[PDB]
Image 1 (cartoon, rainbow, N blue to C red):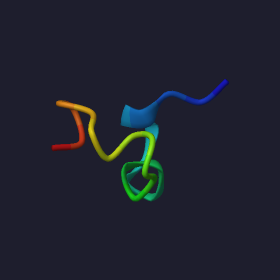
Image 2: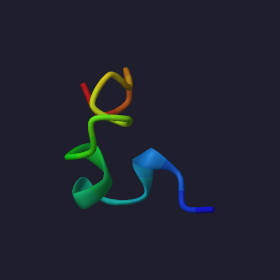
Image 3: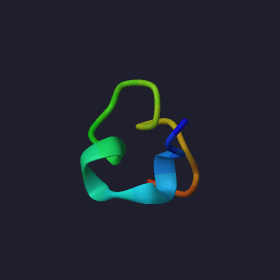
Length: 23
């Protein structure tokens, strides 16, 4: 599956929002 640091769109996910990579 696609990681959270794959694109900004993913960073806008309540699941990837708490990700130090997206934060």
